[PDB]
Length: 389
Ligand SMILES: [Mg+2]
Image 1: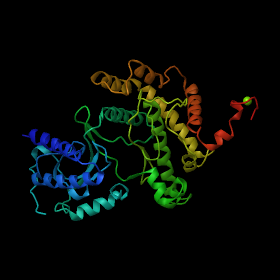
Image 2 (image 1 turned 60 degrees about the horizontal axis):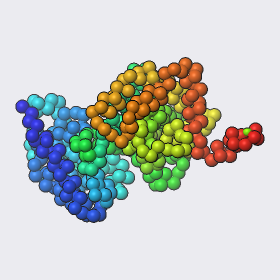
Image 3 (image 1 turned 120 degrees about the vertical axis):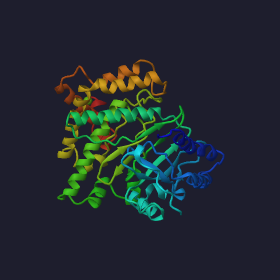
Image 4 (image 1 turned 135 degrees about the vertical axis):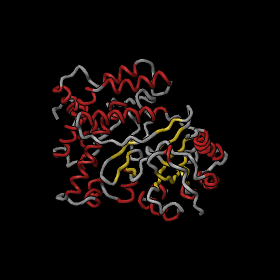
């Protein structure tokens, strides 16, 4: 039978490492400790233990100790590890694999990292070898992240059911204690910040260079991916009221999708903004340009997807609300503030509106999301003065 004590000890071992990292002040010293800690871990591998974020049956065979990184200098600094596993068909009928004798991490292309680690590993030759990643957070409450994950998965199910081609990428969350857990990061994606820094290009010119020129299938495909993911995250950001959007917490993948990460401030999280914002989702000049501009066909597609996505969401509203209620009862998180949280969430599904009214609302919301475009300061004085322009 599959024993749970080995798994418990495995997970505990990852969390124990963090307490020892906390004894050191700088990220550099923490990283040095972490490498040594993971080296010890390999004494006990392979074993009948698994990474629950895998999503497929496997055994852990190795942790490439030199490849792990601590992410900051905080007392309970997150740390990122890579974990080698051997996939198996059926866990409970598979034997434990035999042991085989023996800044850049974030920017570096995933396929390059997989290549190097595979080359260095005694297990890298096996066809069922896979590389996983987790970020261990010993001092962060991840229950808000878990709630977001659950809601994001439900929206994907809803959009699939309603045949709306919105795209999002939920990332897996394990809640360990009330103030610790793990995350499976999104790989093969780079923050918008880093893409722009390394390339010194606008997003459009980056797309043109990386995917292809205007007349190419690759450009159009990438543009479509961008639009579908933009619309998906627009709706995520609105319905869950995700704050603190910037180019550090929006990632771009190799297919042209954007991916929002870090839902620290959702629903009734403090501080509530004072800027009369509908959402922290912003549509910048750069983003609109990737979509072919304000009069662009792909921008029109964006707006259509937003409408159809919202129609789909309200059609299945109870499936989302239930998730949030189940969490609110079981826990007591800072994203909740009494009974107004659920009321306000339901109100964002606009159940009283006709689809005609919803369409007008979407036009309004999209206009709002573009308010920080310089042109808006330039071209909206009719609302601020008795002039008609
Ligand atoms: Mg006026």
